[PDB]
Length: 83
Length: 83
Image (cartoon, rainbow over all chains, first blue to last red; front, side):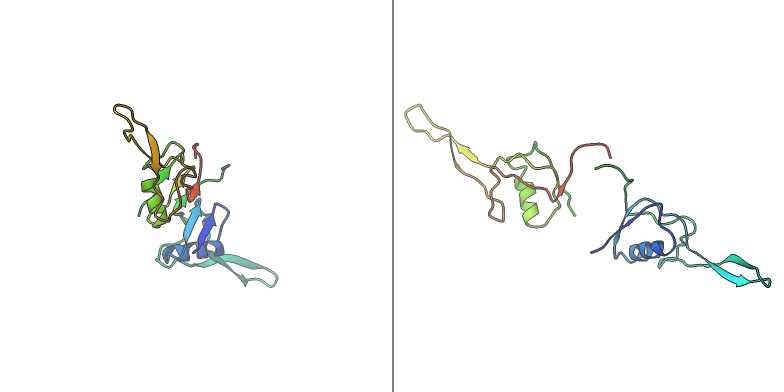
């Protein structure tokens, strides 16, 4: 058994696991909505000493739905607080 | 699926339904510890018009443990409050 905890501070790779497991029903995502990330920033030179960091592609979760920019909705939504 | 809720104000076949499901893994008891009260009382006549009210037997949960006066310990323990 698995139980992944996510919140508004999770991005990119931490959303791939939290979304591939949820789409495969391999875990229960608990927490809040995740920080929308999931775009790769390829660095390529342009000038002799300067370059550009430009978004090139985005990767989508096993279903097909995209991380940008909705994020992951946990199955059991619960905000942080005292027990 | 089932999800039973119990509280310290439950007893006397409120722990037969909760206890039997818990021992058969048919539900997930949630709440606080129940008020331990398991016993059978009868009114055996002893004299012409005098009788005694004496407990003779209790009911033991499917496992074989007793309700009086341990009660039912929920699998998930929480207390009343605002989420």
